[PDB]
Image 1 (cartoon, one colour):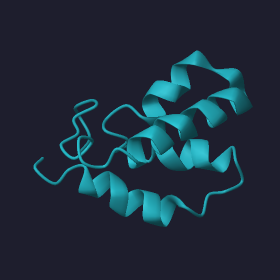
Image 2 (cartoon, rainbow, N blue to C red):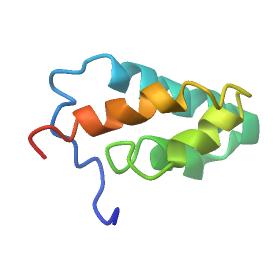
Image 3 (spheres, rainbow, N blue to C red):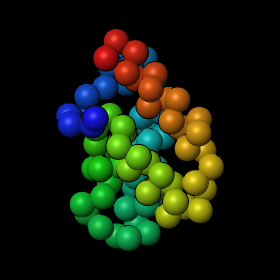
Amino acid sequence: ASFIDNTCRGVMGNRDIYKKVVRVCEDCTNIFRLPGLDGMCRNRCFYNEWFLICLKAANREDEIEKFRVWISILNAGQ
């Protein structure tokens, strides 16, 4: 289970899921305007469903499927 943090491995190759992810947290962070949220969103290498939480604040809650497999890519070496 998720018990690490920013424990990525592909965040070096991705260079896309990150910029987007981290950016996805910002958006949501605004919805609630909570400082203790952005992190979670892109905390444990973005592996904690914390993505759906923010993705929801954007009604999107759809790009999670593709955003999910992505978070898994960063776990390549990991």
